[PDB]
Length: 308
Length: 308
Ligand SMILES: Nc1ncnc2c1ncn2[C@@H]1O[C@H](COP(=O)(O)OP(=O)(O)O)[C@@H](O)[C@H]1O
Ligand SMILES: Nc1ncnc2c1ncn2[C@@H]1O[C@H](COP(=O)(O)OP(=O)(O)O)[C@@H](O)[C@H]1O
Ligand SMILES: O=C(O)c1sc2cc(Cl)ccc2c1Cl
Ligand SMILES: O=C(O)c1sc2cc(Cl)ccc2c1Cl
Ligand SMILES: [K+]
Ligand SMILES: [K+]
Ligand SMILES: [Mg+2]
Ligand SMILES: [Mg+2]
Image (tube, rainbow over all chains, first blue to last red; front, side, top):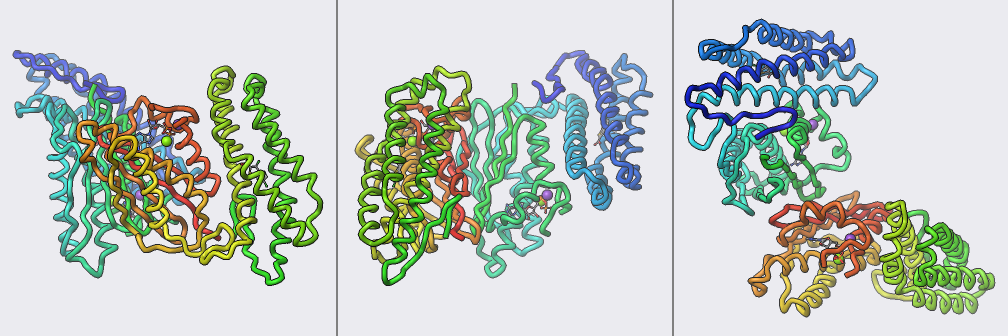
């Protein structure tokens, strides 16, 4: 089973030798990908790269490269176990990176000449980071013995169930802010189950659901106690999984339409939900498409390729 | 009120002088547009242009140019009235032109080197023809005194009502072929009324409805007596009119997706419905977009700009 330019190992050897193979693989893969991202930071427009917060993330990436390269060759389970400590630390050290980049770039990007430069930098940086985090988490998860998982790969993911999980989460945030939340109905292939990697859905779904719920409440300020449902349709075929999220939140206005996919743009939480979700979907071989019915609502279509 | 590179006059003079102005306008506009299309025929790949049916349409276009240019200057109501006879004849003489081109091109296009050449020829020819027919019909309709119309412009078009008209039509064709037809529900801005030109909708709507109904029946061969509804949503805003037509007919397969917009392509009536509808929508400043949920259904979105 694989993803773009990387593979997620589904080993299961008794002596635990698959952990050594996995670890050695990480050590030959992660430093290269970190190095590529450091180059990304090096080539940022000077005035952006000088931003203290951007510099901090840059330094963090240098540190990560240094720590991995300083780690001795993995020869035994004792080494592998310490390697896992390093991986856990880095995952934790880097958990706020998306937020730091958003902040650092927010002001600094208003300065430079080329406007698609930041978009390209963020698309490339955030997707490479997702890949890095997936590989690292997969390696850790190989030690686990949860049913239905091989590392971070779920062998029988139910899209309805993971959708429901994020629905409950988004409904709670929405209720806290507006005193109510749209109900969500789910239809189509509600009983589908198939091998799949949850992690990208764990980012994308709450972003799209928050969007749809905010849009619904903000357009029904007179009747917060009675708002139209959000309707989610699951289509599962041999090629891809499609999740359509349809709201009656009034639509994306014509004057806003060409901006909603830009990092930082927002009508309101830092305006990253849509461009990030799209970059993730595309990184994984899928896509994220919007259909705006101005005056009525929006349909968002998430497509993710099935596992090979 | 206007459309691309042409205007539809909303005159109403008592002496009937607006009919003379309209007629003179046609005589200074139509011959030019016919001449442009004749050039189109002249530049067709030799082997296609030699097809007897293509030659017939070519000749028909030459004849139309010849008749209009042979018609004397319009100076009085007596002239204008005879001019209307000529216009009616030509409209009638040319009513099968789309069908003739489809047939003539069907075989001949398999020969030539450039594959997007025919697509371009048909997009340009069919849209210029729609423009010609709109102008000509508008001029004729100026003699009429129907309530709510100025020529072919409806001053208070109800999208729900025109949708319902074509729904009944498509349901009857479908019922005759399959012994039943999906019901259609219409929601969103069901009470919208606004100035609008019906003619393009009169072509596009039945094409999209036939598609959705065929797809629905062909995927429910076991239960023809109980098939899922087609659902149409109307969104009316200050910029455009959006009509979403959503079916549970199983979707457009991945292997077919990149072909359904090509003239001539069909899984079955001559495979012109979709590319023609899209060319018309775009000619008028709108668009036609498809979202396929393979295994479930298809959403088709027709957008047409409001009148200026
Ligand atoms: N379902 C929706 N309905 C209406 N507007 C939306 C919807 N989803 C996104 N938007 C618009 O696109 C903008 C960008 O969204 P996003 O990238 O998620 O950033 P944020 O939600 O933080 O503003 C939103 O501020 C909102 O104006
Ligand atoms: N709503 C739909 N659902 C499934 N397939 C569709 C739908 N609309 C169009 N298609 C597919 O696209 C093809 C092209 O349609 P069209 O251009 O209207 O030509 P025709 O209907 O004559 O085949 C159809 O044959 C059908 O396979
Ligand atoms: O930026 C990030 O989120 C992460 S997590 C992470 C984990 C490892 Cl083991 C190495 C680099 C790295 C980076 Cl860079
Ligand atoms: O091709 C067609 O449909 C038509 S209708 C029509 C009507 C007039 Cl008056 C002139 C040309 C012309 C053509 Cl070309
Ligand atoms: K945004
Ligand atoms: K076609
Ligand atoms: Mg958001
Ligand atoms: Mg058709």
